[PDB]
Amino acid sequence: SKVVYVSHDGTRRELDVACGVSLMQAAVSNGIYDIVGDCGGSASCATCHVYVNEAFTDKVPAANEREIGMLESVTAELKPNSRLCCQIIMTPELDGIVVDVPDRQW
Amino acid sequence: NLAPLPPHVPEHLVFDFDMYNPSNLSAGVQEAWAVLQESNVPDLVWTRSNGGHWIATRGQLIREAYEDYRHFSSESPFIPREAGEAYDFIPTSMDPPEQRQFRALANQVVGMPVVDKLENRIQELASSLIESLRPQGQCNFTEDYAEPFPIRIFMLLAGLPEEDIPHLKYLTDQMTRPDGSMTFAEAKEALYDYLIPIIEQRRQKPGTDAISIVANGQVNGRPITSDEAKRMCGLLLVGGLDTVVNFLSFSMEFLAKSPEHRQELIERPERIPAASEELLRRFSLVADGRILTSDYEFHGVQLKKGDQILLPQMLSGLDERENAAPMHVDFSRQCVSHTTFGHGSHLCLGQHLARREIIVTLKEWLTRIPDFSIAPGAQIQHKSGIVSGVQALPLVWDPATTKAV
Ligand code: HEM
Ligand SMILES: *[C@H]1CC(=O)N(CCCCCCN2C(=O)CCC2=O)C1=O
Ligand SMILES: CC1(C)[C@@H]2CC[C@@]1(C)C(=O)C2
Ligand code: FES
Ligand SMILES: [C-]#N
Ligand SMILES: [Ca+2]
Image (cartoon, rainbow over all chains, first blue to last red; front, top):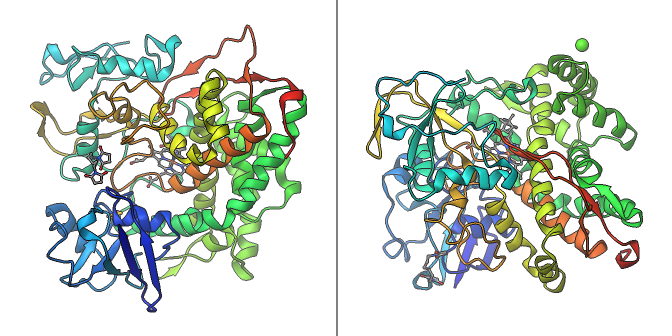
């Protein structure tokens, strides 16, 4: 499987993510400093905020109650395709998903 | 000393457990806590010890409680009996606005980007200390490596010069070790007065070391005060110190008795990151908790506001419902599940630095001292508490089996 992280400046980071790994853990484990992941991935901090490409939004599992109430706290612009990437678990069905990383998490 | 049973605690939930002196401690502290997970023990028990408090024994309840901001506090009511372990360098009366700002500032100091950049120097530090012990054929790993290593790592982060090593080591030693005629406040104030001149200095002309970043931080739209800055530096130095020291000793104690696990990592060093996560599960060592902020029925048990509830981080990974054969150390374990750094919004902000210190330690030790064992006739003693630990780890090896790298 493969995930592409598009930073705020347009820089691309194409990354091979193992099945069962969240988009946060992959980013944090692979030098993607623009994703913080302060709480370790339990929808408790909103420092893994990413914008999901509109092609994959309807494919990824939807957000639960905790993620939405936590998404209200994002410091960047909250968009309808904003997600907590620690709640996006990688499966082969999501191969090629692109996420836009905001200019800030803190 | 056993506290009276509150009127809402049914008798069948009462369990004999003293978190500072568990009965089976000689089998190992993790094993002593696992008696809470035997087949006939409820998932949520009450103990008369240490003033009376709940203990959740299963990872599922432990994870849910740390996430449930409605009925469980964010701060721990469990006061460590030692004065040094009870101090909060950032006050508990803080509000979520300030809590977030301090997590952000600490993340600038020990976050994953910082750990990556400093890894090569952390590597050089581990090598230098291990090579210094390699030809001796003997050492107390706790005193001779486990304690100096993270202190020296703080000095790298904080841009402190090497001639301050004996003084800063002595000062952290007065704070962590209750032995010695000096109160914690006097040792803590002595630590502060070492930091204040460097803080005030690097506030004018800063750099990019840890002290400079903290000294130049902003809180509530205004510069961080000198009081806030010294507390941050003190927290970053002594916050992680005890758990890192003790966990390394837990890990090295196991590897000293497990030649087959050592050879597995020597032959396939690419498995050390996975092995470190399996050691973090198996030798988890923190057991803290929260307090109820409102009455709540939790998994069929009536909890009352003000009840203390221990939510031991170490028990989640030892739960057989989470990891089959939980006492088995399997470096190829498929789905390693634990809450060793905690769970929820206050998960250890030093988790990335801590994992890198463990991975570099195992890598650099096994390369130079691939074979070692406990000193014969030695009695390894464990201690139990909020942070459990190893009293001492005397190791011996044959210097001719070692390889200078
Ligand atoms: C094996 C090593 C370590 C383990 C097992 C560990 C475990 C923990 C646990 C269980 C907590 C409480 C989490 C919670 O309350 O939800 C915590 C918090 C904390 N840790 Fe560690 N930790 C380790 C290393 C470190 C290191 C290296 C640092 C370096 C700065 C550090 C700094 C802190 C701080 C400041 C807190 C307080 C966080 C807060 O209150 O927001 N720890 N750690
Ligand atoms: C990681 C650990 C675990 O228990 N777990 C769920 C078990 C089923 C997942 C294994 C099969 N699998 C893959 O290997 C990729 C996607 C998938 O379902 C984990 O995912
Ligand atoms: C109890 C402690 C002082 C020790 C270091 C920080 C602390 C709050 C912990 O969670 C472990
Ligand atoms: S990592 Fe904390 S919410 Fe995603
Ligand atoms: C953290 N200690
Ligand atoms: Ca003074």
